[PDB]
Amino acid sequence: EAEKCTKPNEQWTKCGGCEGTCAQKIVPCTRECKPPRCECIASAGFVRDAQGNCIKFEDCPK
Image 1: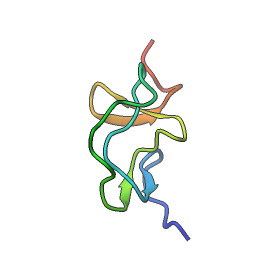
Image 2: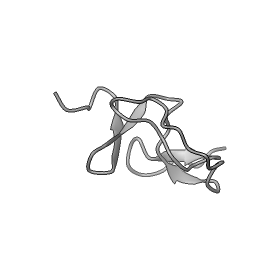
Image 3: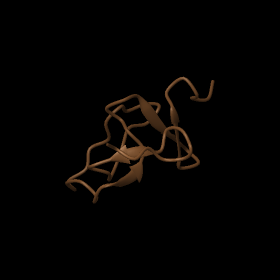
Image 4: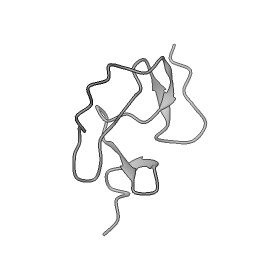
C-alpha cells in the first residue's frame, strides 16, 4: 500500500512539509502539506536533529 522507504524514520507521507523537534513535537507552519513523498513523520514520534536529520525521539541527544 504505502511503499515504505529504505532508511528508517524517513517513511512515506501523504503530507510532508515541516515536522517536530526534540523540543516541539509540532512546529508552527503557515504552509499546508508538501506533495506525497518519503519524509519524516511527527504524528509517529520522529524528530529532526539540529543536523537536519530525522530520527526517533529516543535517538535525541542527551
